[PDB]
Image (tube, helix red, strand yellow):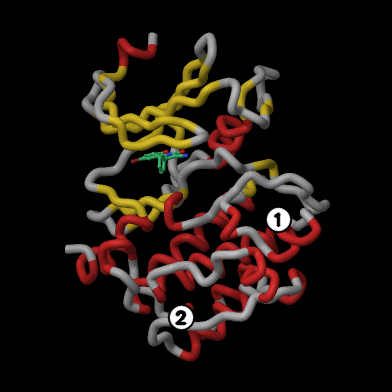
Amino acid sequence: PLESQYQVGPLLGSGGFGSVYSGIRVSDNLPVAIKHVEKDRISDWGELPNGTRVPMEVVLLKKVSSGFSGVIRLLDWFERPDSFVLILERPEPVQDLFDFITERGALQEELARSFFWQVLEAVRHCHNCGVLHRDIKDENILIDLNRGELKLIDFGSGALLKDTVYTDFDGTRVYSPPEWIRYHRYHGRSAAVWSLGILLYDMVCGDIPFEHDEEIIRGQVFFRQRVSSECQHLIRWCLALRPSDRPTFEEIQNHPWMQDVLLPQETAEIHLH
Ligand SMILES: N#Cc1c(-c2ccccc2)cc(-c2cc(Br)ccc2O)[nH]c1=O
């Protein structure tokens, strides 16, 4: 009984893959997010420990659910005749990176460092759990304004992590790597690092670097905003044309610009309060 436990609220947003509403767990007033996904649009299905057919999204979210709240947590889920309904945790107040950057424009490096670092910890968490996000971007990152913690959301274009090549992709095009645009082939980690490269640029310049396929395959990076030399370096490194030339997650976090990151709470007190 879904409608009995939760109290549906306002429409937080929707797209090709879902409609999301703001609900509250009638049980304890817990704030949650209710995501509706139509069975038709669902492309990938999995099963997880049970042998129960469910959309890959549910599989992935279950594999990454844990104490670590660097990634959104699935509280429960229900299946319906023509759709699946997911109950996600919902922080409040909260704002997504896209809206936040859309209001403050380019972010101070110090803040971008904290945020970027947090995203990296989350993505590492996922890979570690055998999950590849495939759609890392400002829109899929939530900001818990009080604790200054970011959360990865929307594993709708995700997939189990593997070492062999990927031939499918349904994530955001402007965040996809050169190798996808050209050969429609890519490898998880390297493809991820490339989008992390687009994300960082996005944070420090206030907008993405590439808009057209040509710009992506060319990979020439121009900075529209004053950006430190160190940050520019890490950015160009993540956006290297050749996949194998991109940094490992370990190399990114050991990069000079990534040092002395602020604690989440400090970040909130200085940049969010
Ligand atoms: N797709 C998607 C998704 C969202 C979305 C983003 C932009 C526009 C419309 C919907 C939001 C969420 C989402 C939002 C909150 Br406050 C809390 C938990 C969530 O899990 N999940 C998605 O999986």
Residue at left offset 48%, top offset 67%: 208
The kind of residue on which mark 2 rests is: Gln
Q: Quadrant of residue 33?
A: top left
Residue at left offset 33%, top offset 12%: 3
Q: Identify the secondary structure beneath mark 2.
A: loop
Q: Identify the secondary structure beneath mark 1.
A: helix
Quarter of the image where the C terminus is located: bottom left
Across and down, in percent, residue 250 comes to: 62, 71
Nearer to us of marks 1 and 2 is 1
Q: Left or right: 29 with respect to 65? A: left
Q: Which residue is mark 2?
A: 259
Q: Quadrant of residue 226?
A: bottom left
Distance, label 1 to label 2, CA atoms, is 26 Å
Nearer-the-camera pick, 181 or 98: 181
Residue at left offset 71%, top offset 74%: 241
Q: Which residue is mark 1?
A: 188
Can you tell me whether the CB of the residue at mark 1 lies under 8 Å from the nearest atom of ligand 1? no
Residue at left offset 23%, top offset 24%: 28
Q: Left or right: 14 with respect to 265? A: right
The kind of residue on which mark 1 rests is: Gly
Across and down, in percent, residue 59 comes to: 61, 32
How many neighbours does mark 1 have within 10 angstroms: few (below 14), some (14-19), or many (20 or more)?
Answer: many
Across and down, in percent, residue 272 comes to: 22, 63
Across and down, in percent, residue 157 comes to: 60, 42
